[PDB]
Amino acid sequence: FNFNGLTGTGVLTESNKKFLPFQQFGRDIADTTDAVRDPQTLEILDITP
Amino acid sequence: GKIQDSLSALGKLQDVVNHNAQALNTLVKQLSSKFGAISSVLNDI
Ligand SMILES: *[C@@H]1O[C@H](CO)[C@@H](O[C@@H]2O[C@H](CO)[C@@H](O)[C@H](O)[C@H]2NC(C)=O)[C@H](O)[C@H]1NC(C)=O
Image (cartoon, rainbow over all chains, first blue to last red; front, side):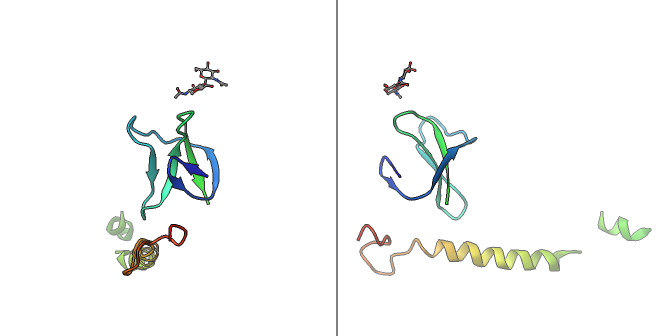
């Protein structure tokens, strides 16, 4: 996957997180991306390894 | 019966958990270091 610049690999699943309208993606503790927002549909998706 | 009152101690057991959690949190964080290279990502290079 690539989400507007974020290059990575993983499984995409429906999330239950809530981003602040200005945030595009989230990171977990230990500073690794764990959720993104689809640029086209504007939905939050978790990334499992 | 007084033993429960003194509990409701186990810091020696929490320290074991903490020491391993800290080594695993540090091991992952050390991947975001350039070590004097142009970048820290083997694909971007
Ligand atoms: C980006 O454009 C697409 C065009 O396909 C939009 O998708 C449509 O959105 C409307 C409004 O809710 C729906 O009624 C349509 O059913 C959608 N199309 C399909 C094929 O499902 C999309 O909403 C746009 N995104 C943004 C953020 O504007």
